[PDB]
Amino acid sequence: GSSGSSGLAMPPGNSHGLEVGSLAEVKENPPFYGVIRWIGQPPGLNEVLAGLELEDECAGCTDGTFRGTRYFTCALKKALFVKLKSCRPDSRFASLQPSGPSSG
């Protein structure tokens, strides 16, 4: 076990903690940010693809449809699918103890 304070780490699993609902980041040329939506493998190519919904409307993306198979419901031009294995936890909106003194 790693020597720290925060646990819930499963490197042997996916990478750290990338699941539906949680924010993640993809390592590519265009630096963008999106939250996970659907995580699965289409009928043909076995690969954990986590559907990320881009906050910014970029021309070229889809409305949450991979290979003509809608997994979730999102806006138009704000759904980019990527390999979950090549994803990174996004702590852009991660909070830890809003206040110091917890003892009321």
Image (cartoon, rainbow, N blue to C red):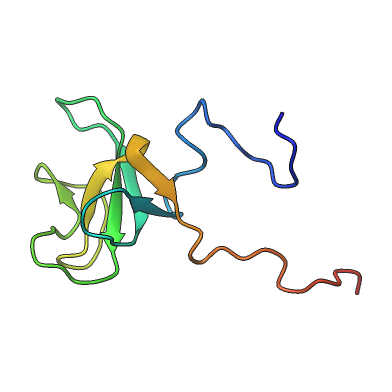
- Residue 24 horizontal/vertical position (percent): 40, 53
Q: Quadrant of residue 90?
A: bottom left
- Residue 6 horizontal/vertical position (percent): 70, 47
Residue pictured at 74% horizontal, 42% vertical: 4
Q: Is residue 27 left or right of residue 44?
A: right
Residue most extreme to the right: 103
* Residue 89 drawn above or below residue 59: above
Q: Is residue 84 left or right of residue 99?
A: left
Along the viewing direction, whichever of 28 and 18 lies nearer the viewer: 28
- Residue 38 horizontal/vertical position (percent): 32, 46
* Residue 84 drawn above or below residue 58: above
Q: Is residue 2 left or right of residue 59?
A: right
Classify the position of the C terminus by image quarter: bottom right
Q: Is residue 40 left or right of residue 45?
A: right
Classify the position of the N terminus by image quarter: top right
Q: How many marks?
A: 0
Residue pictured at 51% horizontal, 59% vertical: 91
Residue pictured at 16% horizontal, 51% vertical: 65
Residue pictured at 46% horizontal, 54% vertical: 22
